[PDB]
Amino acid sequence: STVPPSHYIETWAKTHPEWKAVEVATGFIVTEDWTYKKLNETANQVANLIIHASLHGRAIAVSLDRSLIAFAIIVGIMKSGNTYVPIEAGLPNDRKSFLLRDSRAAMAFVCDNNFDGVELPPETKVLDTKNQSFIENLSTQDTSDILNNYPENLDAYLLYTSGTPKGVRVSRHNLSSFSDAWGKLIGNVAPKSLELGGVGKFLCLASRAFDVHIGEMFLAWRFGLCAVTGERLSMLDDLPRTFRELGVTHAGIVPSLLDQTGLVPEDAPHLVYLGVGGEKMTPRTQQIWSSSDRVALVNVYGPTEVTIGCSAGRILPDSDTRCIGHPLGDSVAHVLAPGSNEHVKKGMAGELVIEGSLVANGYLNRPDAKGFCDINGRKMYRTGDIVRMDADSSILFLGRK
Ligand SMILES: [Cl-]
């Protein structure tokens, strides 16, 4: 058992209510922000709105701009004991319609005609976050913390992955174990992180199509940082400007974006921690970023089905770039013969199979999609990835099964 996903939000709201929790950047730089106290109150109001609609354990879809209230809606959905279902605002209408329907969304928070031309399921109650009436009703809800006593395995979010997309059900326990495991890893490899409460910032750069965006905001809150974000086209336009002008101290990026932009550590003067993942980094990226004594560079392995990042390791100038490090928190990595449940001798190639608190609940209504299973009566996920363990038990990524 674990503290809930919104635990650190509530904790910093009590101990340091004036710290900034979220900030959204315009202009391109003008910004606006909310304190932990304000973020937490608004999320409780959102949660109370949801509870008044009698929704429990229901899919609540969100298709919003990059706004302060978006963050409060996400947290609110989780405080109300319901499931967050991100739907990227730029998706084609047909694909938005499918996600609403497949997820059985009971309610949706939208703005900006993001749902214009989307077929809504009749069950979907649609709230426009920019509508004077919705704002007035929200401001009228109670602001105290919700009594948060939901089962551990209750879904916290549903994240769709690929021609018919399948929904991955991620539990409260999964997400809260993620925050705990990464709080520990990041605090260890980038100790300045424990000094940055109230000052540092975690750049929320990921598209809402990926679980990474959830990780970014909850890791910011874990450490007392400000989650900072903007319209993605605007943040990506001049990536050095974004890191430099928004005071970013922590970020996650796919490394080819470092290559394309020519980013170096001096373009991000406040940066102390840089997670990369999702593809192998190039030799020059490694040379440039792995030798800094200010920035800790960490390679992260993270299928959606195992909650954002379940293995990671610091990358140094002599590290193999296929190394995905060691399992996080209580996770246990096994390397099994691709066709059986038999462990291979350490050092041999085989399929990576993860066990532990980061393994997701499963796919939503996709009985033929494989990967989740019981192996020796424990819950595991077979990644489809071929790896081998190094002598020191770190894991090298070799390819796809
Ligand atoms: Cl929560």
Image (spheres, rainbow, N blue to C red):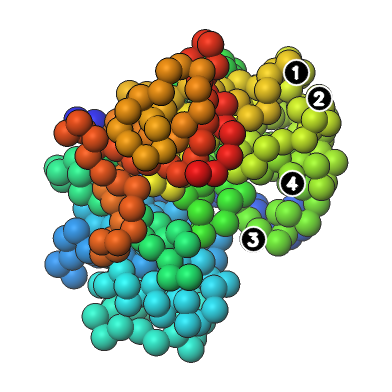
Upstream in sequence: badge 3 or badge 2: 3
> Within 8 Å of ligand 1, the CB of disc 3?
no
Judged by depth in the image, the label closer to the viewer, 1 or 3, is: 1
In this picture, residue 316 sits left or right of residue 9: right
Instruction: Note whether 63 is above or below 187 in the view shown.
Output: below
Task: Provide the secondary structure element on which disc 1 rests.
Answer: loop
Q: Residues within 10 Å of mark 2 (few under 14, many from 20)?
A: few
Question: Sequence order check: which comes first, mark 4 or mark 1?
Answer: 4
Amino acid beneath label 3? Glu
Tell me if residue 63 comes above or below residue 184 in the rendering: below
Q: Secondary structure at mark 2?
A: helix
Q: Which residue is mark 1?
A: 317
Q: Which is nearer the N-term, disc 3 or disc 4?
A: 3
Q: Which residue type carries mark 2?
A: Gln
Q: Quadrant of the N terminus?
A: top left
Residue 5 sits in quarter: top left
Is residue 333 visible in the rendered structure shown here? no
- For badge 1, the amino acid type reads Pro
Residue 267 location, x and y as percent? 81, 35
Q: CA distance from mark 3 to mark 2?
A: 31 Å
Identify residue for label 3. 231
| Earlier sequence position, callout 1 versus callout 3 | 3
Q: Foreground mark, 4 or 1?
A: 1
- The alpha-carbon separation of the residues under discs 1 and 2 comes to 6 Å
So how many labels did they put on this image?
4
Where does label 4 land, which residue? 257
Q: Which residue is mark 2?
A: 287
Instruction: Specify few, some or many for label 4: CA neighbours under 10 Å numbering under 14, 14-19, or 20 or more.
Output: some
